[PDB]
Structures are given as structure tokens and as C-alpha cells.
Image (cartoon, rainbow, N blue to C red; front, side, top):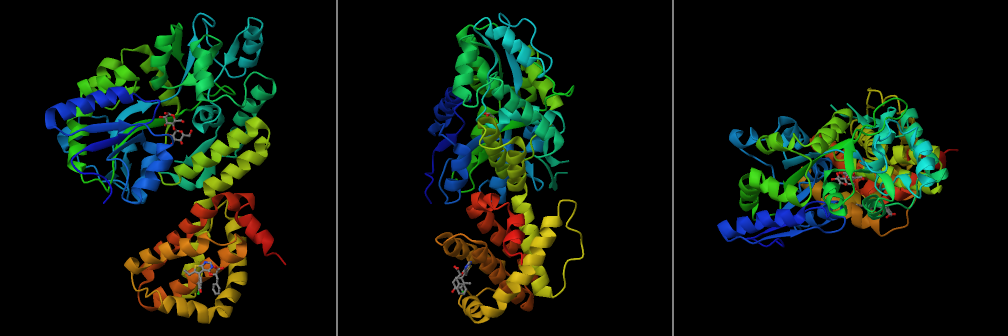
Length: 515
Ligand SMILES: CCc1sc2ncnc(O[C@H](Cc3ccccc3)C(=O)O)c2c1-c1ccc(O)c(Cl)c1C
Ligand SMILES: OC[C@H]1O[C@H](O[C@H]2[C@H](O)[C@@H](O)[C@@H](O)O[C@@H]2CO)[C@H](O)[C@@H](O)[C@@H]1O
């Protein structure tokens, strides 16, 4: 077991109030003798799943609720079991964001939404519409100033515009069959952003650091940022307001709402100290004030302390923008949707891809997991039982049908030609229950990993998976077919993601074996 016992390590993002969090760790250490280390590593949302998976990493991880469903799906988080007394101290909707398969997987800390931030000295009336920002930039450019600068490297900041005229991630429970990443509304919003860049009103290269510096030295009239950014603006002496985001096509910008949440590592031998630090030290008037004094949290989940901060108009603007937005879903494929949209916005902005090209590729990566499982689960199940699934694939399922048709035709030959080799490998792997199926996964990455990438090898993997599903059903282990399909899908899309999207995904597969 790698994680040290008798002490707490905390991971929190570098835009957050980590010095304030460390003051609450000092107060925990002063009362219990347990040293709390707070770190803010780069890409901790990428690195937590990698190190947690091997029993390593921090005791507590802080991030918006959107990444927590994937970590729970991978068994990287402890179940949070606060009593009714502690649960009543926080807003029920904040608890809704940290509930996954009916289990609390984290402690909610604060509701974050993007607002529009403007220089009252340059722009006494901020724009009501996105459409008027070009004329405003022209006007401010004559004065050696610019209208707007925000981070174009993170899809988070651009999403409100993309979602305004009907863009969305998963239709709402959440329908992961229904992805709205390349709909007319999404094209309209992202096209308007590329047009601002084309007409020199914004810069494709602008990241968080550049946008913050330009706003805080009064070079740009406007930025798009969250509560965490107010501290640095306070220091900079800029007379700023926090207001409702400008509308697009007469409709509000819908910011993706995040709930800063604290998760407990499953591998942690200090889960009792972590529960005690989070419930009785951090989630208190004194604890949330210590963190908020460093960098504002936004609208905190703690009712007592949220009553006080509600009077602040910048919080009111945050909640107004939050109402017009959507609570982010916490489902496992959020990570793949964010990765896909990040790439789409960066490519459309730089002109490497068109808005049509970029958003189509992001709609493929957003659907790739569910689309792959649908094909593999149906193939494995129909091979095991001898009867096809009657149910319809759905509205976007023309690809799944042709891909299953191609897999049937192409992959039945592979089962026949490799029968002897498959039987040899299935005998040598002693499969017999869900436990034995857990083993297999480890094998398949090792095998599917260090080899040349082609549709031929993808077919062999799925074909051997069907062969194992046939065996599973034969020994009354038919319930293990759905998890084996999940594991084959997991190996394939987690390791070949970038290749599968370059091949137009399953359309590429049908195209490749067409005759
Ligand atoms: C967990 C087992 C998997 S998963 C997977 N995914 C893609 N390809 C595989 O094997 C082929 C090579 C090959 C040559 C002749 C017969 C079968 C396959 C390859 O790597 O190209 C495999 C194998 C695998 C590897 C070695 C073997 O001897 C057997 Cl029987 C198998 C089933
Ligand atoms: O940009 C995609 C990104 O969006 C959100 O991350 C936000 C985070 O929620 C905020 O707390 C803030 O600090 O900035 C981040 C933007 O870089 C999602 O939470 C995150 O999962 C996703 O990758």
C-alpha cells in the first residue's frame, strides 16, 4: 500500500484558494497532531485516475463534481456516509451533484458558474449581446483597448456561447444516446467565436494567463471567469463588475455549472481523518471563510455561510448565470466529452479544421464509448445465445447497424479460422465467473497494447470476446457477458481513442471492410 497512514495529503487546482485550505490543515494539525499537506499539481484531474488506480495518490481530491462519476465507476473513491445532521447543513441540490448510482461519492463545497467580468472605467454599460461585441471592439481598439479576452484553451469558457442556441452534452435522467455537440445551435455559437478570431476581435492563442493579465492591467474591457479570479482583480485595482453573460441569438449563454467537491481516495488508510477534516474543519463558517478569503469559492454548499455571502452582488450574478446554465452531469464519459470539445474549439479557432469538421469529430469522441459498447455487447450476446437483440439501435444508430452487420460478416470468419487458438487461450486462462473476467482485461491491454493498430486486430479482439461469451453462457455465467463487453470496449476506446476518431470511428470500420 503506497499512501502513507497517520497524515492527510490534499490535491486542489492551482486557481483555487490552496493557502486558505492549508490554514484549515494547520488548525486540524493544531487540534489532532495530524500533518495536512496541500498540493496543487498540474493536470490533477488527469493524474488522479492514473495514480489512484494503482493504490497511490492523495487522501482527498478536489475538483468540480463532473469528474467524480468516472472515478467512482473505476472504484477510486470511498462512499461518503455523513449523518442526517451533517447532510441538513448543505443544500440538497449540492448533494445531488455528488450522488452517483444512489451513493454520495464526495462532499460538496461551492457552486461555481462563469460570469462576465467588465472594467467599469472602460465600459460603464457591459454588452447585453455577443452580436454587439465586434462593434464595441472596433470602438475600444481606436482607444488602444480591446473588448474581450478569455481562455480559448479550455472548452469550459467557450461552452456558454456553444450551448446558448441549443448546444448541449447529454439530453435530460441523462440520455447518453442523445449528444448535442454538432447540432445547429453548437455550430452557430462556435462559428461566432471563430468569426471573432477571423475579424481579429479575439486571438486563438489566448490562454488563462494572457486573458487574466490583459484584464487586470486594464488592456481589455471584459473577461469570462469564475469567483476564484476576483482575488487577483481586487489586487490589480481595476474597477470591475460581475454581470449576466451576453446573450447569443436572443438566448442566454448557458455556463456549465460545477460544484467544487472533495473526494476520499478508496486506497486511503486515513478515510476517518479525511471525513473528520472535511465535515468538522473545512465545511464550517471558519473553514469555508479561510478558503474563500484566499480565492472566492462562489455560492458555498454550507447553508449558514451561504446566507452571509448571498448579500454580495458578484455571488448574485454567479447564481443568475448558474440559473440560466445547466448543472454539469457527473457521468463517466464527461472526461471524453471534455477532451473532444477541447480539441474541437482549439482546432476551429486556429483554422486547422472547419467548425463543421471539428464539431463532427467531437460528436464522434463524445459518442464513441456508448457506440462501441452497443456494437460489442450486441455481437457478444447474439453469438453466446444464437438470437439477435430485437430492440432498436435508435435515431443515430444507422452506423451501429452497418458496423454490427460488418462485424458479423467479417468476424464470423475469424472465429472459424482461429477456433483452435481461441480454445487454447480460453483453456489456459481458466475463465469461470465475474472474478476470472476481471483478470482477462489486464491480459487484453498487454496484448492489444504493444502491437500495430488496424481494424483487423480490433476484429480479432472482439471475435475472441464473442468466443468467451459463448463459453460463459455454456457454464451458466451469462451475467458475465455484459461486463466482458464493457472491458473489451474499455481497452479499445481508452487505448485507441485518437486513432478511432481519425478513421471516422465505426463509419470507418464499415467503409474499410466494404466489398
Ligand atoms: C487475450 C488474448 C488476445 S486479445 C487479442 N486481441 C487482438 N489480437 C490478439 O491476438 C492476435 C494474434 C493472434 C494470432 C493467432 C490467433 C489469434 C490471435 C494479435 O495480437 O494480433 C489477441 C489475443 C491473442 C493473442 C495471442 C494468442 O495466441 C491468442 Cl489465441 C489470442 C486470442
Ligand atoms: O475545460 C473543460 C473543463 O471544464 C471544467 O473545469 C473547470 C473547473 O470546473 C473550474 O473549477 C475551473 O477551475 O476551471 C476549469 C476549466 O479549466 C470541468 O470541471 C473539467 O472537468 C473540464 O476538464
